[PDB]
RNA sequence: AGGGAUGUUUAGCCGGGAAGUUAGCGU
RNA sequence: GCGAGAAGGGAAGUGUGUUUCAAAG
RNA sequence: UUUUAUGAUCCCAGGCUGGUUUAAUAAGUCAAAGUUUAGCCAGAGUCG
RNA sequence: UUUUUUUUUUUUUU
RNA sequence: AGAUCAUCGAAUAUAACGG
């Protein structure tokens, strides 16, 4: 049954004032038993580009068919500004909307568990699923066809610019053995899309592959800002020097690295960094490694190399964020050749 | 499904300025044995 | 709630009874006679949904014009046969599924086809 | 004049425009935006990569007879490309060019 | 004239094609990626044309006929063939590649290319292979050998030998490096 | 008593490739 | 590993072309 | 029910465009209904 | 299901 | 994506759909 609507794409001038937003709801329908709203807030105290509206107790709203819903939707769609979406909310998706707001607030808090070297070759990705996803919903998966009881509160999801649940979903595993087993059977799988009317929805092919990693350390933020083209390599043999051991053996292979770094931690595997001058040299290196991997019979899915990147950060007392900067000119370093 | 197969979105946006192959390059793919065929890359299945 | 499941075997009798390919004129009248859809659905109701669903284009129903006319059929009418698309067994199945739900969601509190709306 | 053999113009693979789009989000001109990929498709390579590939037969024009008279001495004419997967076969051999 | 196509040992009989490629009559400058390499100054495709089917009259058949692989010249003996006759299948040994007598480096059409330096007017550090696990599929020229790859320094002796290295652990036991030519070891 | 004795064939899924096949409408 | 029809007139009449606009895979 | 002298049915042949100076109170401010020479767009598929 | 593998994985019951 | 005279060969015209 009907339980409320869901607004999106709202202008910043209406979310920052509760008086204006409340006035628009009184004329269309019930005023702010009266209805209630809930505005999503970020960790820094900033609002979002969407809101939520909840209807009164079901006692006075159970008998509401499509005839009364079409008129209400239509009438409440005109009062707000243009370029706005006003969709209905079912009984199942209503509970999921609350979790969406909580994920945005805990985005930075949740990106610390298993991110360090402790859990390196564990993390996985699968950007198949659409916005329709949940911790509970997704828990049933990877159990009926792969046999793998993954943790519950270890599920992280990214977000787009409009605080919308990005299709990029990331999972974790308790152990390391089962990691490989996840990315071998989840290929071209069609469990379901949506559970409406007691029947399944459209089809969706699954595709799991290791293409992204996470790391959190105190000696990684500064070193990874000086060079423009920085590489990452791992899965090395017993403990080694930089100038005396890493440089000498590098001559055999084709790394062609200007500089190098180390990665302590006291584990049984090392990981030395690499540096390049031009983007073409970096690019060519990627191919080389890839080719070599096959030769060695290491594994397609086996993490061997990667590209280092700096995650976007949002500071305080700033009128505009770095990620939302339209005047940035950080693309000239990547020349195009064809 | 039929029009467009399962193609990850990550590999579609990046492949933008990729020049299409020529006439002779096309025959290489079509030539037997088709060793350039990847996983789930079959044009018949 | 609890929408009934349409058995494949049942649809075979209706499709073959109205008679590989068949015209769409005889199928529209036979669907209502069997009463599988259950107000009473009128003949115009099915025709309106057929055009609104963009089934002629999807199914490539206009490809038969070039066989008779040829080059003259490429141009628009003003810049011509107009026979309906002859749906096959496979094609007809899809349409029946699509029209079965379009009538149930017309009075449901939670729309399924088009839930969104632009201001 | 009934059941007369007509002729249609030739058309090769249309190259996609650089300035394309994935999905037009409520377009506000009187037309459809072009595509980057166009006719071409992206597939997984053997060595774990992504590369272009000639799609399934691109509208093999059967209306016009072969130009070189000496085509049967080196190539088998009247070919068919069928799609089968285990015990399932689909009817898609008719390659018709619909009107604009 | 080019040599006739032949199938290698361990392969079922195939049907020969009527033309080398699709554009046989029409085009002539087009070349297939899988073209044979028989002209002097090239190398075979390993497992496509290296070991074609061998036949001989009944009279010529003998034990020694089967041992042709193990008696190949130094310039054509691969790792697989070399390890087959060594004690313990060449296990617990060292191997290295000597790139000094390649067919293209002495003979061939493009045997006078201009290098970045020009011409050669005049102790090294060569890689060493330690085979650990040996698995033979198609003897004596086929195997899946897993070993530890490391670096070692050569000696001052007249021949190519390995004094007190390998020293550094490069990578865990992996697949072989090269399949073209290999030398002996100290063991 | 040794020039003896002992040893003998491992199983399932999925993706791609070559030859033969290219008969099916029973879903 | 990458490039290669760089030697193409065989098809089409309301088509091939031109002009006005548009295109954040 | 639809086209039809504002050419419907219908037979043969022809692929579209640009190219700077250029005399004379036709003193062209773009060479004035239609004239070209490095050039743009465009030109199906097949080893069963 | 049968030859080819320098693209993979799985095997237990107090 | 919209718009965008047709000409020569002397000429010879009403045709296709449903009761």
Image: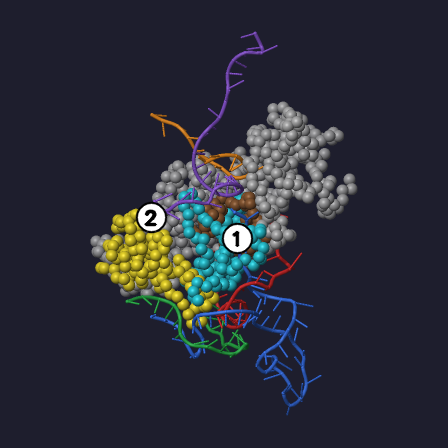
Chain colours: B brown, C yellow, D cyan, F purple, G red, H blue, I orange, J green
Q: Residue at 25% of width from left, 54% of height from top?
A: C34
Q: Which residue is mark 2?
A: A200
Which of E51/A21 is in front?
Answer: E51
Which of D66/A303 is in front?
Answer: D66
The relative height of residue I4 versus residue A198 in the rendered view (above or below) is above
Whether discs 1 and 2 lie on one chain: the answer is no
Instruction: From the top left corner, tell me how far across and down residue E94 is, in percent.
Output: 64, 29
Dot 2 alpha-carbon crowd within 10 angstroms: few under 14, some 14 to 19, many 20 or more: few
Taking E36 as reference, is A235 left or right? Answer: left
Mark 1 or 2: in front is 1
Disc sitting over residue C62 in the figure:
none
Instruction: From the top left corner, tell me how far across and down residue C43 is, in percent.
Output: 27, 62
The relative height of residue E129 versus residue A337 in the rendered view (above or below) is above
Q: Residue at 34% of width from left, 59% of height from top?
A: C23
Which of J6/A32 is in front?
Answer: J6
Taking E150 as reference, is A35 left or right? Answer: left
Q: Secondary structure at mark 1?
A: loop
Dot 1 alpha-carbon crowd within 10 angstroms: few under 14, some 14 to 19, many 20 or more: few
Instruction: From the top left corner, tell me how far across and down residue H27 is, in percent.
Output: 64, 86
Disc sitting over residue D77 in the figure:
1
Residue D88 showing in the rendered view:
yes
Q: Residue at 21% of width from left, 53% of height from top?
A: A59
Q: Residue at 24% of width from left, 57% of height from top?
A: C33
Taking E174 as reference, is D86 left or right? Answer: left
Q: Chain of mark 2?
A: A
CB within 8 Å, label 1 to label 2: no
Instruction: From the top left corner, tell me how far across and down residue C20 is, in percent.
Output: 37, 53
How far, Cα to Cα, is label 1 from label 2? 46 Å
The relative height of residue B18 versus residue B36 in the rendered view (above or below) is below
Q: Chain of mark 1?
A: D
Q: Secondary structure at mark 2?
A: loop
- In which quadrant is the N terminus of chain E drawn? top right
């Amino acid at each position: 049954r009907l339980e409320g609507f869901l607004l999106s794409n709202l202008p910043p001038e209406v979310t920052n004032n509760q008086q204006l937003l409340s006035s628009l709801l009184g004329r269309s329908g019930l005023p702010v038993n009266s209805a209630s709203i809930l505005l999503q807030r970020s960790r820094l105290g900033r609002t979002a580009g969407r809101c939520l509206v909840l209807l009164p107790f079901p006692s006075s709203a159970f008998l509401t068919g499509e005839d009364r819903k079409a008129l209400q939707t239509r009438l409440a769609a005109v009062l707000p500004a243009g370029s706005t979406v006003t969709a209905c909310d079912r009984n199942d998706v209503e509970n999921c909307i609350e979790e969406f707001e909580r994920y945005f607030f805990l985005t930075e808090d949740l990106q610390r568990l298993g991110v360090p070297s402790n859990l390196r070759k564990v993390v996985t990705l699968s950007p198949v699923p659409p916005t329709y996803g949940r911790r509970e919903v997704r828990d049933l998966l990877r159990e009926h066809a792969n046999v793998d009881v993954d943790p519950r509160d270890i599920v992280f999801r990214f977000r787009k610019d409009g605080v919308q649940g990005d299709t990029c979903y990331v999972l974790c595993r308790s152990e390391r053995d089962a990691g490989v087993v996840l990315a071998r059977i989840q290929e071209t799988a069609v469990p379901n899309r949506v559970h409406y009317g007691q029947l399944f929805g459209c089809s969706f092919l699954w595709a799991s592959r290791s293409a992204l990693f996470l790391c959190d350390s105190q000696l990684d933020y500064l070193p990874a800002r000086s060079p423009f083209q920085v590489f990452t390599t791992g899965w090395e043999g017993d403990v080694s020097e930089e100038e005396f051991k890493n440089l000498a053996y590098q001559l055999r292979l084709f790394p062609k690295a200007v500089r190098k770094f180390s990665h302590p931690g006291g584990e049984d595997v090392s990981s030395f960094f690499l540096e390049f001058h031009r983007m073409r040299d970096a690019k060519l290196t990627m191919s080389r490694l890839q080719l070599l991997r096959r030769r060695w019979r290491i594994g397609a899915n086996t993490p061997f190399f990667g590209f280092l990147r700096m995650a976007d950060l949002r500071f305080e007392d700033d009128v505009k964020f770095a990620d939302e900067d339209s005047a940035a000119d950080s693309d000239l370093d990547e020349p195009i050749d064809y | 499904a039929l029009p467009n197969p399962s193609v990850p979105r990550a590999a579609l946006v990046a492949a933008r300025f990729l020049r299409p192959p020529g006439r002779f390059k096309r025959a290489e793919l079509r030539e037997h044995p088709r060793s350039k065929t990847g996983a789930f890359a079959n044009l018949v299945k | 709630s609890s929408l009934p499941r349409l058995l494949d075997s049942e649809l075979t009798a209706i499709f073959q009874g109205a008679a590989i390919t068949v015209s769409s004129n005889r199928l529209f009248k036979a669907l209502l006679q069997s009463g599988i859809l259950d107000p009473v659905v009128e003949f115009q109701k099915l025709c309106d949904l057929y055009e609104e669903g963009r089934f002629y284009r999807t199914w490539a129903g206009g490809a038969h014009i070039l066989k008779i006319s040829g080059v003259k059929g490429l141009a628009p009418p003003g810049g011509i046969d107009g026979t309906p698309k002859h749906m096959s067994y496979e094609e007809f199945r899809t349409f029946v599924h699509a029209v079965r739900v379009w009538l149930r969601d017309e009075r449901s509190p939670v729309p399924l086809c088009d839930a969104t709306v632009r201001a | 004049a009934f059941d007369r053999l007509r002729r249609l113009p030739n058309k090769a693979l249309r190259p996609g425009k650089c300035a394309g789009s994935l999905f037009p989000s409520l377009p506000a001109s009187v037309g459809d935006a072009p595509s980057v990929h166009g006719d071409f498709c992206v597939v997984r390579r053997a060595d774990g990569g992504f590369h272009l590939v000639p799609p399934y037969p691109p509208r093999i024009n059967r209306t016009v007879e072969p130009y070189p008279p000496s085509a049967g001495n080196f190539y088998e004419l009247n070919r068919q490309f069928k799609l089968q997967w285990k015990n399932v076969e689909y009817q898609f051999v008719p390659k018709l060019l619909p009107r604009p | 004239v080019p040599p006739p196509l032949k199938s290698g040992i361990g392969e079922p009989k195939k049907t020969g094609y009527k033309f080398p490629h699709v554009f046989f009559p029409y085009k002539s400058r087009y070349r297939s990626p899988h073209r044979q390499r028989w002209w002097p100054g090239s190398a075979p495709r390993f497992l496509l044309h290296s070991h074609p089917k061998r036949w001989a009259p009944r009279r010529d058949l003998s034990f020694a006929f089967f041992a042709f692989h193990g008696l190949k010249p130094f310039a054509e003996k691969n790792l697989y063939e070399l390890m087959h006759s060594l004690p313990l299948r060449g296990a617990s040994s060292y191997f290295w590649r000597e790139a000094d007598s390649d067919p293209w480096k002495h003979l061939g059409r493009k045997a006078n290319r201009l290098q970045a330096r020009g011409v050669r007017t005049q102790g090294r550090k060569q890689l060493v292979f330690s085979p650990r696990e040996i698995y033979y599929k198609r003897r004596p020229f086929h195997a899946l050998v897993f070993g530890r790859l490391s670096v070692g320094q050569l000696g001052a002796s007249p021949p190519e030998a390995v004094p007190p290295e390998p020293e550094r652990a490069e990578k865990p036991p992996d697949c072989e490096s090269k399949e073209q030519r290999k030398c002996a070891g100290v063991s």
